Amino acid sequence: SFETLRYAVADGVATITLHRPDQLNAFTAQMMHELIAAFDATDADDNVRAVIVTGSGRAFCAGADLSAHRDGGGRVSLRIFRSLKPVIAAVNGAAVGVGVTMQLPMDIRLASTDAKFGFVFARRGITPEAASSWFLSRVVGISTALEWCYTGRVFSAQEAHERGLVRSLHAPEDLLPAAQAIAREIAANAAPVSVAISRQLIWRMAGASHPMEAHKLDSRAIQSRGRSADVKEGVSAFLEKRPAAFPETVSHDMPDFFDWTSEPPFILE
Amino acid sequence: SFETLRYAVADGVATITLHRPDQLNAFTAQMMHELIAAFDATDADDNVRAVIVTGSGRAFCAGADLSAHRDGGGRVSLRIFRSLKPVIAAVNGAAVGVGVTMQLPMDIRLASTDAKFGFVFARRGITPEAASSWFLSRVVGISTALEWCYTGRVFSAQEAHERGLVRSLHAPEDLLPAAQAIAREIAANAAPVSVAISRQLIWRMAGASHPMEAHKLDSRAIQSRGRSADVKEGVSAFLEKRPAAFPETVSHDMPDFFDWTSEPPFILE
Amino acid sequence: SFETLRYAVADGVATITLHRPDQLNAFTAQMMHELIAAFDATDADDNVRAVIVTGSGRAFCAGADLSAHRDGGGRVSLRIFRSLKPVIAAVNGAAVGVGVTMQLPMDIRLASTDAKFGFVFARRGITPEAASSWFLSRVVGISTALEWCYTGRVFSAQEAHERGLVRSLHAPEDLLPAAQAIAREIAANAAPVSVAISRQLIWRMAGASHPMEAHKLDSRAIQSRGRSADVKEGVSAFLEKRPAAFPETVSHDMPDFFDWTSEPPFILE
């Protein structure tokens, strides 16, 4: 139960709906705390195998309203980064300021053909936040990140897709069905512990200085999964001509050799 | 005043013109010192809100002529990296050897349809320089970087654009107008301190191991800009139906919590 | 001489052929040791100036059969990473599981129009290996890496090329000729020491936190090559209207200021 979001779980898929639509879902202190609580709920709910984030009304999110000195956007961004479930943004409308910076830590961005995007910070005399200086170059590459943040231009879904911010474009009526089809295909076919480990190694090894770091972690991951009941279930089911019902859960069966919840310290100098 | 460059400031835009055209603007010791001095001038001139780099004559730059044991190309590359203004390359002609490696630290590459590019080092029995082993993978990605440096092939503007070295292609007469329209749109719409912080965080956080690093810096940046006169000017101007005249300057008003001029030590082992 | 591979050297090009075709070249303990030995041979053979890896029969490689607790895939991946010669994958058929993760450390991926690819780990209750959590984001970028590993979908050559896993697509009969034309153009035109240094700096500086790291190494590399006989041979040959016959070799003439064979320690916690 939230004031700034709707939250629904159906068919193994959580939908978090940004829900201040009279304000084009403008981001507030409470949406920040609530989105952190939404991801705590999705990480803990074994019935959740994928998460869709979308906007109510016309917009996705048009921007921010008006020893934790921490940017609110960043707190959400860092929470999603250490998320254990697939996260898909279904961008239905304007995603401006923190409204676009919030999507960069999500795993897959789908956009309505109506969607608009703008890193408008420099036009307002402020700066890109939500750790977008880290995320944005790893989605669209440095040159595009610099051009969008320098001009602060509001650009089309078509530019978003050509420059690689969004995976694919959908008719307004087709967006959530598309996000759902991806979410359900993961929920149907993949073992939730394997998905959670994959998510964490891909995101975390993007900042690693050498593939040795990945080799050390992914050696321990494949050793642990190799001895798991999920691997056995995968064998049985193929032989017995049936869809696997992976039994191991993100809530209990996450391998203990690595703290999937860990993050470096927030310290000011 | 320079021997190897022209330097002009009009309408908030600096144009640095590589200017040894009888030698296809071949890079020399003096062009190196002069380009460092050109960026010192652009960083210090509050009338400069964007920088265009271009070539005189037929070529952009066809290559190098013939306890600082430092590659000259790198010295320029590292100077641009810690630059505080948007830098756009307008590649008018051949950009060979250090002539292409010099553009990779710039923020946006525009090319004439006449432009040609070649990382020809290995064909001459030498090696890619100007820290291109760091920059080139972050523009075009590792596989393309390897292929261009292995073959040393001189390739077309069209390949440059398809593989992502250049943002866009222009008729020879359209190149500088296009570079100018981008430069003027930044100079017109964005607060110079916000642009300078954005530039530095995007480039610097591309080497950061985790988004926590960006969150720490961009929390301090948004706190500082939040209390700035630029933010106020942005409010006034919207209400009073007028273009903002951001008053804070890169020369004085750069926030002091981070040394924007800092770089790691050059030490030989 | 190998049981799981064919190995041939012609015209300066080594071809390593994955060769358990009755098993769609499934990866085994012995293919792992043999591929390490194949790269030791290619690194030491000055007659080898480029390496092509390809599959026998219908498939490239359909997956794994069935205080070094090290993933076998990773051992190959890490060996290729510290390889000194250009490595091109010619993907002739299905490349599933470790069959696709093995290609990511190679320098250039060419695919037959018949080729298929799938990161199917999560569908089998296991996890992406061969340090693919490091390599895959640096080939196709994080969002695509996440989508392929979450769904475990087997996808077409066309998707592989559009999302940037493969450089180019070839008719089945055209694949090895294309891989050869690239290999021979390197073998013909580039100095082997320059190629080996380039390979190592591009791959290693992709994990470096700042371009200063590249500037330090590439300053020493260009100083050393500047005094080399290859550079002289390059001068003579241009004047004397003839193709250079670079005399310096990867076996003897690798500059000594950096250990090209070095890798960080494999240690379990």
Image (cartoon, coloured by chain):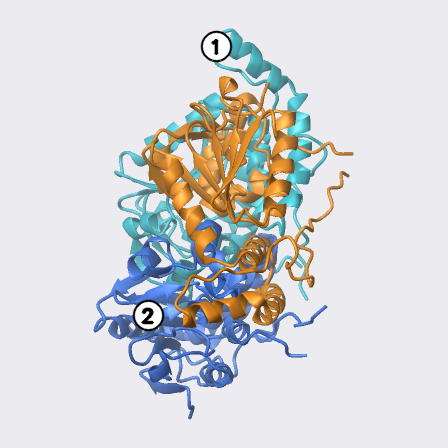
Chain colours: A blue, B orange, C cyan
Q: Is the N terminus of chain B in the top left, top right, bottom left or bottom right quadrant?
A: top right
Screen quadrant of the C terminus of chain B = top right
The answer to whether residue A94 of the structure is visible from this angle is yes
Q: Secondary structure at mark 2?
A: helix
Question: Please, what is the three-letter code of the amino acid marked with disc 1?
Answer: Arg
Quarter location, residue B33: top right
Residue linked to disc 2:
A238
Marks 2 & 1 on one chain: no
Q: Nearer the viewer, residue B109 or C14?
A: B109
* Residue at 29% across, 57% down: A158
Q: Amino acid at mark 2?
A: Phe
Instruction: Note whether C247 is above or below A138 in the view shown.
Output: above
Residue A210 rendering spot, x and y as whole percentages: 60, 52
Chain letter for mark 2, please: A
Q: Subunit of mark 1? A: C
The Cα–Cα distance between marks 2 and 1, rounded to whole angstroms, is 62 Å
A266, above or below B198, in the image: below
Left-right relation of C252 to A169: right
Q: Where residue C133 sits: x, y (%)?
A: 50, 59
Q: Can the viewer see residue C45?
A: no
Q: Of residues C36 and A138, which is closer to you in this image? A: A138
Q: Which residue is identified by label 1?
A: C242
